[PDB]
Amino acid sequence: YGGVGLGKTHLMHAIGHYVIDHNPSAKVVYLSSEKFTNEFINSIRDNKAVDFRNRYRNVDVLLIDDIQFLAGKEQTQEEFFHTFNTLHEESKQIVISSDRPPKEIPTLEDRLRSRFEWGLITDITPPDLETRIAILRKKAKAEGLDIPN
DNA sequence: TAGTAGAAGTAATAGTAGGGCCTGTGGATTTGTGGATAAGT
Ligand SMILES: Nc1ncnc2c1ncn2[C@@H]1O[C@H](COP(=O)(O)OP(=O)(O)OP(=O)(O)O)[C@@H](O)[C@H]1O
Ligand SMILES: [Mg+2]
């Protein structure tokens, strides 16, 4: 969890890249909770629920954006609860990002809130001056431009 | 043949006629009072 524009999607894209590079047989899936809900509901409407479960319960690593989007949605929260349960039971990896810690996500069931706190919860804070300059240096060097200090 | 469990929903107008009056200074205004003035005798 952390602020916006703070590096969470970068971090877990890096996780996916690392896992794919070191293990090519792994089925690493990354998406956003918005796309999760859209696919879930469309599968319900088109009788594709079995295929949705097949695609999402059997991934080796799962990466979720902005799980805050699930707040206020009951059935999608239940379906993600069951997906989490199946993946954790199969000893698979689940990575979740958010902008708020799970304690203060409204309209969240206590089972999901306790599952979120089960593992390790990490926070991102706004960068300071040295790392701002270092980030800009990295972007400038990757792009290929020379710019004064 | 006897048959299931289903969600996440928006950006919204134009709008009425209205009570006397108990009080109460401020100031015009419309005259009476007095003064100025022509005349005529
Ligand atoms: N050390 C760093 N820390 C944070 N951000 C960094 C760092 N180095 C580079 N960035 C850049 O920060 C930007 C922030 O975008 P990012 O996708 O990470 O946002 P976010 O806060 O995780 O949001 P979201 O989950 O909605 O995508 C990226 O474009 C990334 O390239
Ligand atoms: Mg992004």
Image: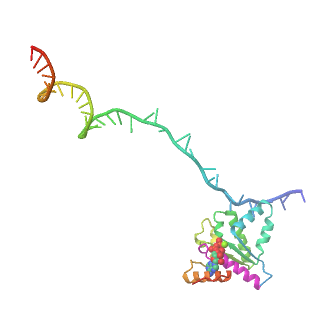
Inspect this view and state whether residue A120 appears. Answer: no
Q: Find residue A19 and report its image quarter.
A: bottom right
Query: Which contiguous range is marked in magenta?
Result: A1-22
Q: Residue furthest bottom?
A: A22
Can you give x and y, in whole percent of width and height, for residue A61 in the image? 74, 78
If the picture is divided into quarters, which one holds ligand 1?
Answer: bottom right
- Judge whether residue A148 is colored magenta: no
Q: Is residue B3 above or below residue B28?
A: below
The answer to which image quadrant residue B34 occupies is top left
Depicted A39 relative to depicted B16: above or below: below
Residue A147 image point, x, y percent: 61, 82
Residue depicted at x 63% and y 65%: A71
Quarter of the image for the C terminus of chain A: give it: bottom right
Residue at the image point whose x is 79% and y is 71% from the top:
A55
Q: Position of residue A7 (x, y in %)?
A: 63, 77
- The answer to whether residue B9 is left or right of residue B28 is right
Task: Report the side of A6 relative to A88 (left or right).
Answer: left
The main secondary structure of the magenta stretch is: helix
Check residue A21 for magenta coloring: yes
Foreground pick, A97 / B19:
B19
Residue A48 seen in the figure: yes
* Residue appearing at x 73%, y 64% in the figure: A38
